[PDB]
Every structure is written in structure tokens, then in C-alpha cells.
Length: 330
Image (cartoon, helix red, strand yellow):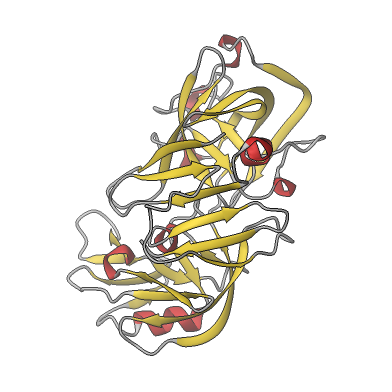
């Protein structure tokens, strides 16, 4: 089997991407944030505290004839951005773009933090990291991809995120018309539960490529590119007037600037992020200072190849016996 669904930026800055997902019988369609950096499929629901729901579409398990409460199961997750959610657990039928899993754990939120309430465009998350990170207790549950894997034509999924434009998540096949050149595959460590790999270096604009190992994670649920302070300083040094702002919490730059591109290495191959992908717009409404899309990972403990990097590439998440990651230009 295969599945294919279109993923769409939630706003004009590509702050995140949403993909429609069918849950239950009859289908309830929710727009979920596909997140290769986490492993819980959770949704706003009829159980969510009412004051915490502000425009999201909710899953109502009582209206799904295939929903079954998973007895005694709860979940609670806290994300790197400070947001969180928690609740109970049903199993139900879940379909993405024509691909169907019966018995998928659907984590129904009783509580969400303020940032989720404030984002009316995200109905929940669909985790695509490794199932060892799933938070369901006392019996950990499998991700949608883990459940679908054995049925897929090939044990893979692909992310093709657009810049200011729709894109595609495919399960079970590689669309060889979706990228240019070849796909370069690189090794993955699953020891932290992530799609963790080692970039071979970077360049800023037309500058010299610096060979240096950058360990980090391919994370479709993180907006920006988080890289070591030395690399981020080298990038923003090329932008007249850019500086690191303590009040804003990262590098900012004059909105009148034209940004240089940023290149990262995948083996001997190179992915080029165009400069405009690095512009996240005014720091506050009406400001002429703009937020940068490359920021330091120094306070994180891990580098994050988020959407800024991934949307410059066609990305294969290869769930073969030994998982690997593939990147092609597009």
C-alpha cells in the first residue's frame, strides 16, 4: 500500500505545516502537524478543557463507532518549545492520503498549553520519530508509520515541504519526479529516538564550504534551523546590521536586507537553502527588524534541521531494518 497527502503552511511565514488526517468511523478530518521530532499522535478533542479550545477542530471519540478506550492509558508530552498537552487514549482507524491503519493509538487531549490554544490552525500532532519516544503509559504505543510499515510497498515516508506553497507527505514510495539529481543517503542513530544524523559541513552564500561534523535531527515539527553558535555567527556576520538580541531571543536583522543562502552537506552532496527561506518577518507587527530563521542551538543540547532546512530538500525517512535518511535537491 501507499498513501499521499498534501501538506500546507499554516500562515504566510511557513511557521508550521498541516496535513489532513481522517480519524474514526464515520471519518473526522483533523489538520495535524506531522512531526518527525516526536512520537505521539494526539488531537484536540471533545474532552479538551473548553477554555483551551479556540477554533480547532476536535475529535469526538463517542461519535466514532470504531473508537475503543484504551483502559488505564494516559499520555503527557512536553516539547522543546515549552508547549505541552496531556490526556487519555483511544484506538481508532486513522487514514492519511488513502493509507489506513486500524487500531492506531489516538491520544485525546484533556489539557493543552496556551500556545496550542492560541494556534487555531493545528488540531494536533502526528508523530513520526521512533516509537521509543511515545509517552503513553503504562503501555507505550506505536506511531502511525510504525503501524503502517509492514503493509507499505517500501518501508519509507518522504517529506517535500514547500516554501510559501503546498507540499506532500508520501508513505510507501519515492516519487522520483519530485527532486533533481540523486538522493544521497546518510546514517541515522536512533539512540535518542530521533532521526539523528551528521551533516558534513556548511557554507554561507557563495563562501568556502567548511567541512565539520554537525550532529542533529531531521525535525519537521520545528520551524527553524538550530545550529552551533560558531556556525550561526558565521552566517549572520554576512548580513549587514544583523545582531543577536537578548530581548527578542535570537538573531534579528534589518527587514530591508537580502539574505545570503545557507548550504549544508549530506555526505559529499550539498543542499542549498535560499536566503529568502531564512526571513521570518517582523519581530512584532510594524517593526522594521526581522527575525532570523537560523538560530543557535547552544541552549538546546542538540542541533535541529527544522523546516527551514528540510523545505529546501526532498527528504526520505527510510525505515528499513537499519534506518537511514536521504536528501535530494529539488
